[PDB]
Amino acid sequence: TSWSDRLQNAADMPANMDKHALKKYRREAYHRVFVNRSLAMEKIKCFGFDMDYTLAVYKSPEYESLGFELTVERLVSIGYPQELLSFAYDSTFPTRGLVFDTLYGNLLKVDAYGNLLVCAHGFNFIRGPETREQYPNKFIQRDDTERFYILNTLFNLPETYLLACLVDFFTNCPRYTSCETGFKDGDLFMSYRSMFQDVRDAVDWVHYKGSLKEKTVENLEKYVVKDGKLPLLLSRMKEVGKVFLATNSDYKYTDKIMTYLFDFPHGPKPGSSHRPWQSYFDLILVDARKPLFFGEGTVLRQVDTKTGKLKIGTYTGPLQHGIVYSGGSSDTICDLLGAKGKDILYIGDHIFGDILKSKKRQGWRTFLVIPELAQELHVWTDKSSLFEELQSLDIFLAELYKHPDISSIQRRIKKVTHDMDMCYGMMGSLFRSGSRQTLFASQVMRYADLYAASFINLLYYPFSYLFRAAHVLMPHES
Ligand SMILES: [Mg+2]
Image (cartoon, rainbow, N blue to C red; front, top):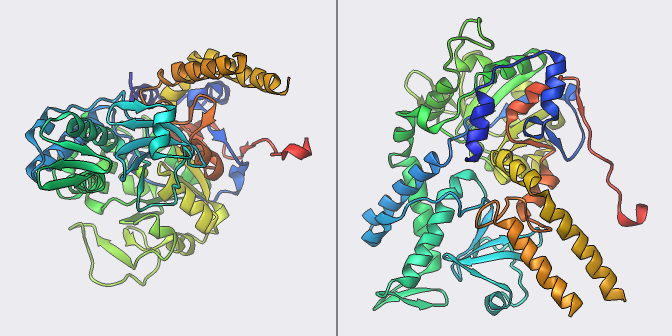
């Protein structure tokens, strides 16, 4: 079972809008909206959406597998060895949010401070003291964006696995000789960083010049989750506020995916006339180029929807029914919809490009969609046992220190941590390794005001609702 399977099964279920059923439904964890900072939904005037992996959740592992095989084939066609074609995507290896160290070829799972939680060279997990050879302080400066690349979105799941496949392949192929920073084959030296760059470029190419979009659009049922409750939520949002779309995808792909997402024999609810997807939005903006969108942006353009090409020139006119925008900036949204940042709930899946930047740069309210959360929640409850253990041991270890045994328990902690981590996958949970929270976890807590397995979970809350977080206290305040 994949995380998308739980999403698809919830998506099959029609909306019972009886108010008692909604409170019952919302209190199950899979359907709940989780709260880091308090948000009074009554003060929200604009609900804004990203598309890919927010409204349009690609099915797993089919979509990653397609992206993987198309990327491998691109690498082979530019000259990588034919043995790459025998690679097959394996969904149990990659966890999202890993850091690839382009200097030493390692995949790293780090905490908010750059401390190493897991280090994997190819498929060989480097433990404790062996990592100190390359990481003397067991720590990396993630600010060093020239050396480290954070694989932050679900689109990066294929290359996460692919990078490990390649490091493993070149390490164990006898034509190549291993060095600290790459592989030599006679007079050709392939550094990990140039290998990383080829992988990044092939992923980009597959998405923007190869066949990924075509193959997706010609079998949408295979690749994209569909949910009849989407038009209902959006029309309800439209009753109390304005609704807008702001996506990095271009108009043609956006049109094809959104038409699929609303392709039901009805509109908001069964029985209602079907309406075009564009009628659910007061503002539609494509080619957003987030996160730049939340700073200077680019020039505001108008899409020719008959052709899907941009009209020549900068659009200077008013908000007008039927118009589709391209580029612009977050200020375009604020001016045209007459909103301030704290009037806006922006909903998306990119912790950096959608959530961190809109929060920090513009003061928008934020809702982070985490598709994996459905499966993470399944594992976290089912295996609460080892976590409570882990909490007990650290507490007991402290009392030992102030009073063998300590060395025995440090090893017992390490064994439990590993046992807990292996139940999510080889790279462990999205949110932690044992008792240590991941960088991704800390960034969710810091910048996502709300978060959920799906944006659809908002349907189960009235729009007067005050999402309440606990007041935070410093250690001395208790
Ligand atoms: Mg997205």
